[PDB]
Length: 321
Ligand SMILES: [Fe+3]
Image (tube, rainbow, N blue to C red; front, top):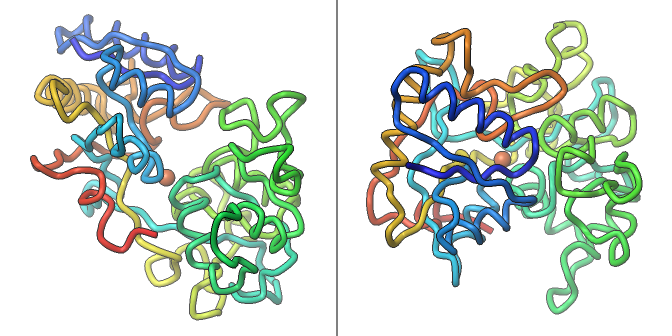
């Protein structure tokens, strides 16, 4: 029986909901362990206290190094059901009717999904590297992006060490700039919320975020995309206007006694019984109102098995930072 690692209290509530719905229809069992961050779950999985967790590209990287050595066993599948993909597009959204392009971003206000995440850090900080005042190590990269943008919200960053990076974060007290749902500018939806609220000028998020979060068509029209050739196209044109195409979030397990057939059998049947438009009792790719992407991404349509003997580095693609 597969033990999933829940990162927050609403993830755990979904996990327990998942567990009782699996027992209800005679699927393979799933138990639940609770932890406070993605790194604690990576550590729990390698310490044999958990067996699975869905991670973002930046954390798939960190799970694949020693002493953890976690490996991707199942990628999340996005796109439509008639046209699926195991990849996403890191984009930079801004309010329409603007002067600026990608190269004139100095001194503006930035909204990020989190420190060391794919579309919100690794990708945009990599694309904007020529524009920075970086002389290389041992100076941390945070300090140079702290002089670039006048204020940001980069969740997970140091409030003491880089105060400018947490300034636009809207969390209260000990949650402001925290890497969790308690900070409301955290993740894809939170970073988009930071642009919507007029706090930042640009949000570095993925391509579907404005289609998810803005159900009303008039308001999606108020935003546009900053393409890397230095032009501005609309939000429906991400396929030609993006910072990078990045590999999808994957479930990671141990590379030694990882139980990956058990993990897959649980995922295939969970997708079959509780996928997009399957059951009205449980949704594996939906979350309750006010919460976003618990356990897996909302509106992902399924899973795809990673072939054997592929580690984190082979998964991430050659051409990573
Ligand atoms: Fe991501």
